[PDB]
Image 1 (cartoon, one colour):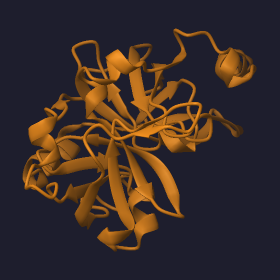
Image 2 (tube, helix red, strand yellow):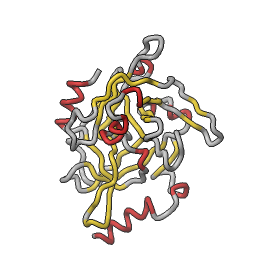
Image 3 (tube, rainbow, N blue to C red):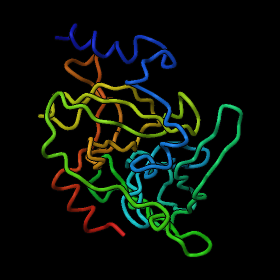
Image 4 (cartoon, rainbow, N blue to C red):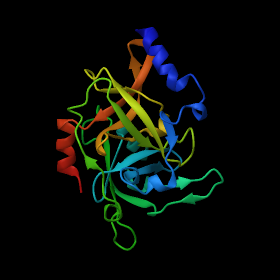
Length: 237
């Protein structure tokens, strides 16, 4: 089953990412970016440090990874959130909702071993919160997910294309030890929203981790389980 896993992993990584089939990995087009849930997805930008993903989950609250937030060193001035940013192939960058400053970083409110962080945004210069312009993501649960389930991962695969929202179909596997799945991702996908067919946020992509043996790997995310949901409800704003 290492050979089974190698074959399956190799469907996403055995070819160059531009040659992946569109059902596994595709750019979100302009029309789709304006619709839910794509419009909840933004670029978490720590200038000079990292460029990754976050999900708008509250009126002023973005959910991302702890490992992304940590690049800011507890300094909100170092982090911006660029919802639905798009840089085209010819260098034109659009930020239809503007760029949002960060008022507070909650680096590890779920625990240091849970790779999630909350970024609290300032309103815009007119006092408009991002969540007034965009309905935050509907928060679901990971409790009903099962091995083999198909989900959509949405985020900013920086290392593939800069500031271009993409969707990746993921396939859950071996959930006994967290949210694990096959799918194409790059480091910039850290913080990508994982959505079910009903558009509910059920997880956040984190990173790749060892799988089956020490020489193989799989994608890992943080599911919106009972604990994560409790903290979100406590801290969201």
